Image (tube, rainbow, N blue to C red; front, side):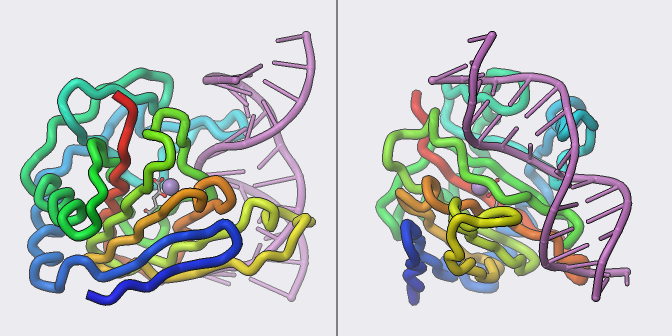
Length: 204
DNA sequence: CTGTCTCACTGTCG
DNA sequence: TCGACAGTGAGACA
Ligand SMILES: O=C(O)CCC(=O)C(=O)O
Ligand SMILES: [Mn+2]
């Protein structure tokens, strides 16, 4: 397996196709069968005083005994299922990084998306990386420097763009999530679903 | 109280 | 139709 080292000012990420086509195909099928996504309040978000559905399905899974913050609430992730443990194990076996939690985001097509954000690190093990594993449709992913955002950016730091392919792993290492925002922009020409798993190491 | 940060839509311009 | 870009606030903090 070949790794791409993604580097810029305050950006340190690595990218590889971690699962080959056949394995990634099987995993995608099993995720589509088995993952249980949020419904009701957890699938709603208020933005600028207006309520909308979250523009992607979400779920969490993790180790027994864990809790996390999401919406309004302190919540417990669902118990691991084997397909998720298969993925986690291969990530940990290759990288030596260990994870106790995963956020799953399912993008039905190019109209599902996630706006520019930094992962909330408050309840994460200090300095821990986040492993982003993708199955299904390739989707464009964008890194934008925190001081290069908006109408009149303080700095004109180059955006870093890359497609996240079927079976790929993007490792995002400290201090990427301090200095850079990332997003999965709307791509209306993408008609097929994508399931993304972001593994994290949360505080007990 | 006191700031700062966040989430995603809709409308306009091309 | 697509998309780039700007503009929109209430809630959770430190
Ligand atoms: O779907 C992706 O690849 C990004 C998801 C993400 O950044 C997140 O949920 O924090
Ligand atoms: Mn993220």
